[PDB]
Length: 291
Image 1 (cartoon, helix red, strand yellow):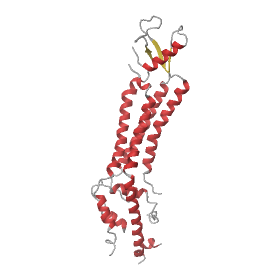
Image 2: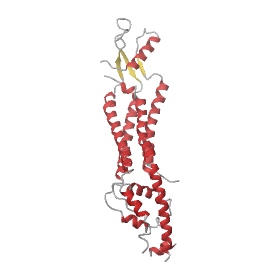
Image 3: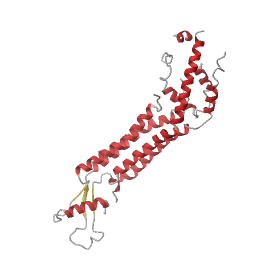
Image 4: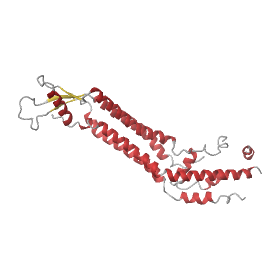
């Protein structure tokens, strides 16, 4: 029943994955309802099937003559790609960091409990500093590594990079097609030319500009909101974490803070409820700890 993810990262992943899916569903469920996502004012003597042909041709082309409006067609697929892009760092953390850290937390929790139990017999009263050789050798070995701190940094770095990519994509493509609801589509380009019945230019109107605007604005707003929490999570480990065995923990509590020790200390602090935290909530001393 161990908890292997910080509470903030859980809600960050949930929001970042869920929101593009919700926006994509809000766009799929409207164009199926309204029918065609584009209308065209065909001439009066175009019967019925020719009007449908004009509609389909202008929707397929999507090129304003008098310049290109391709983002309208590729909205839900581009939104769906964002879901996979957000889900990739979660998969990386799931399949690259949690197996080692799970064992590293279980072992340290068990031996911390054992050390507390051993110190209990000393409480009811110095062969204590050397009494835990494992807690010094193992912790010195892990402090010199750089194994999974890199993955923890790189997950948030990837999330920030993809957020920046979304910013660039939106601000470079969707901005130039705002407030553009109609365009002059043409079909007299290929073999249909040299045929006098069809007019030269046909006006057509997009029927889903509101969905486009709402999706763009909402996505920009939420991915703006989601940046400070990400940078806070990234910068959380930069400052040194401070709250018998805890004395030995504080003994090697110094130096550059970029190790594997900081992440396991953070996960230990976030999982303090597993071990006996009776004395943790009450922040002489031996008399109080006697009970």
